[PDB]
Amino acid sequence: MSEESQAFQRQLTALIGYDVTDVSNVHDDELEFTRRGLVTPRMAEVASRDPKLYAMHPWVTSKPLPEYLWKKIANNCIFIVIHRSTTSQTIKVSPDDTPGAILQSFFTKMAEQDFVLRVCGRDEYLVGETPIKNFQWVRHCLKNGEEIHVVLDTPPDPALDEVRKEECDRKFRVKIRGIDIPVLPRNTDLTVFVEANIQHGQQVLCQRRTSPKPFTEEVLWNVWLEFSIKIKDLPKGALLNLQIYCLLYYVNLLLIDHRFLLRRGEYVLHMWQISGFNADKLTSATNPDKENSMSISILLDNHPIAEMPNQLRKQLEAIIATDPLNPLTAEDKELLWHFRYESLKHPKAYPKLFSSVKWGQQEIVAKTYQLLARREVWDQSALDVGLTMQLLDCNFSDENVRAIAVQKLESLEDDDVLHYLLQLVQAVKFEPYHDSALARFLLKRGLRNKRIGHFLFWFLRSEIAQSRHYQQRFAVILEAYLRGCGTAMLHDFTQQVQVIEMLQKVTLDIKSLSAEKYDVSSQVISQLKQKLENLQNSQLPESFRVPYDPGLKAGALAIEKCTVMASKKKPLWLEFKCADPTALSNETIGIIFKHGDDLRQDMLILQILRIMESIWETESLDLCLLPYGCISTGDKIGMIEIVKDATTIAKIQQSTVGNTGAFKDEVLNHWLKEKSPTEEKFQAAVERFVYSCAGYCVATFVLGIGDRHNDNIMITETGNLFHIDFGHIERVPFVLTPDFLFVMGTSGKKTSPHFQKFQDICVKAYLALRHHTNLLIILFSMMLMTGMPQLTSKEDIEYIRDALTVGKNEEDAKKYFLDQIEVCRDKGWTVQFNWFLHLV
Ligand SMILES: CC(C)n1ncnc1-c1cn2c(n1)-c1cc([S@@](=O)C3CCN(C(C)(C)C)CC3)ccc1OCC2
């Protein structure tokens, strides 16, 4: 390659955090094969995008204006404050007017046609053939009662986005030679054996075991494990799962490679160790640490192409109506399979139908592909996100089954792709092969829209930086995106990466300078300021896009306002000046850098919270959640958005009584009244407290994270309650302590108007979520599988079934949640005290 070609690859390696040209941990060429394969999908999307619209990336929805936003429009009139340098003029606009129309009514209101409306202080453009009511920034201002402020400037030049040009009927058997680990402690007396499983979509097609032997550094067997399944019956995507029991170690091997070739020859596989079921157990990558890991040595030596009776119908309809977690009896599977063509008429049956396929039989697999040829009902069906996500989880390894799921995602608009982007990225872990329709879909949508591409960058990079199991696959996908996003975005990502990596280093250096066991000294703060002083000059980039808020550009550090938080983790509290002079306020941009909690769990929770917001929006319900920004950037390290004018509920308590323990009921209401500028703003804060407390009580109860220490609950000075710090997990279903009830005017068995409103809001929000039970269940199970240490498959996932009271009518569901509110009233301060004791 050319000299600049090598320098460009080094540029990509720095952005990715991993060298895709490094081949220290591969036993085939699938990764390089995938790099070539993703060239055509990338270039096809680069060729299809409009240069002007890609440069301005308008954030737009097609959903109707919610009712709670329509009543916020007084006279079918929306006010836009248009700025031109130091001047400003207010314009009345119809909710259906387009940006081009309101631009015309602006110049006409005077008495060259190449200007653009941009949000003041943000890289957010109000352009395109779209009603102004369908811009997300307009709806954000409507919901929060902010004035729509816009500047009149020049569109960004699409030339900046330039992309650089490219340049056997025999039974299956495996020989288990032995296992090897370099060092083993002298002590104890341990036995060990090897379990060999043929797996497809977590179905165990066949299983064989070796004999148990004493556990030494080298254990040898030299046995043939002969299975009953024939070679010609091995489905594509099937895994040879090898596991050592004393479960201690595991490793997987694709029996059919990316070229439809049966795996053959000698293999020395370095295995993963179980830390003292989940997505990591499905990876075909081997342990990169080949010096100290357990290895297993095997030998492979063994090509593809190329009406119901009314009572049985009732049983089938009952099977289809059950939740995605309901286990399928063998009788149920034979029912779904034999009445194949009736099951095809029910889109919600497809997950259970394909779980009834005998994937270990080639003739049955062929019958399944014949079934999917007549796909009229599925192609015409309305897009069901939850249904589609079921077909992309760990239970389906067939490429054609997963392909028809990705086909349905193609109709998602950019607004909804952003809602599910994080989950779709995680679902790549469930793909048997590196190059898949799901991976190409993500690549496609990220290249089509700069906001999707921005979050796709940081979602992929988060896994690359800390997931040994999937960093190789995600790095090839990220490289494919970076080679098509354009020069301007490559420049932006470079500025962001250099900033976060410099701040990551400062974060780790500060935490080693202090201890959780002790308090924050002026010494530790002085160390921080000196380190930031060295970064600032020199050299910190002049500005960078905020990773969790790409519309915001942060400038220089305000070092005088930077400090180390008094928490146990000693996270950094950083504040940056805003680099956009057209901004309305001189407010700083606050960013928290924290080590070390798994912020990937925070990411998953906050994204589900935003999904619950969209669910409630479709029912004209506003619950006033506050899903702040949060992005994991490495192993137990990442960044968090600073919400202004907010404090923790524990700090409000301790402001009065101080490092106990003995919580008081009236302190929260006193705090809200003190922080309220007027009585009118105070009453609005209490109203916002009622809604947000109900929204979080319902949301945290469904997700099973309701029992929280009030140090992890925050409140804004404008009354917005919100939970924080999810990288963690007598009892309570949620937090509804006497201080919360006092704000609502209630104190121990005394129903107040605000508390009755809280009860009615909770029930309505709860019933609204139950109409999306299957969606919430699939998001919940996927979250445990891709974000948690280890997941019990059949029980941990079972909690949300009872929480969503599956199978009960709305009356029993309503009483169920009202009883949960009563448990909190009966428990009082008890559970909070036990949490405080747990943290003394
Ligand atoms: C608690 C922290 C471990 N954590 N862990 C995970 N997630 C979080 C988190 C998330 N958020 C916050 N924390 C947050 C905290 C505070 S207060 O703690 C802060 C108030 C300001 N003071 C100064 C001005 C420096 C004296 C210090 C204490 C204020 C605003 C916040 O933004 C909302 C999102």
Image (tube, rainbow, N blue to C red):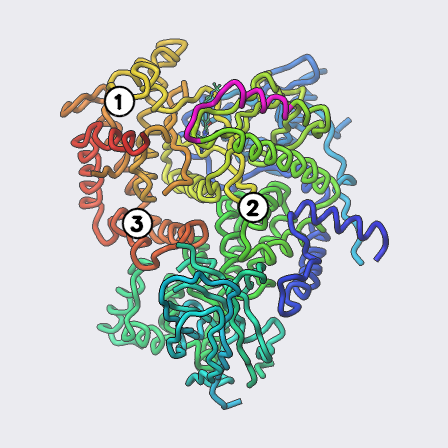
Residue under pointer 3: 800
SS at mark 3? Answer: helix
Look at the image and give the residue range highlighted in magenta.
516-532
Q: Which of marks 1 and 2 is in front?
A: 2
Residue under pointer 1: 739
Q: Split into 4 quadrants, where in the image is the N terminus?
A: bottom right
Q: How crowded is mark 1: few (under 14 residues within 10 Å), some or many (20 or more)?
A: many
Give left or right: position of 211 versus 741. right
Q: Where is residue 692 in the image (x, y as percent from the top left)?
A: 35, 29
Give left or right: position of 64 versus 475. left
Q: How far apart are marks 1 and 3 (CA)?
A: 28 Å
Q: How crowded is mark 2: few (under 14 residues within 10 Å), some or many (20 or more)?
A: many
SS at mark 1? Answer: helix
* Magenta highlight on residue 442: no
Do we see residue 54 in this rendering?
A: yes
Q: Is mark 3 within 8 Å of ligand 1?
A: no
Q: Nearer the viewer, mark 3 or mark 2?
A: 2
Using the image as rendered, state which of residue 789 and residue 612 is in the foreground.
789
Q: Split into 4 quadrants, where in the image is the C terminus?
A: top left
Q: In the image as oriented, which residue stretches furthest toward the left?
A: 749
Using the image as rendered, state which of residue 241 and residue 191 is in the foreground.
191
Magenta segment, prevailing SS (helix, strand or loop): helix
* Kind of residue at badge 1: Asp
Disc on res. 462: 2
* Magenta highlight on residue 529: yes
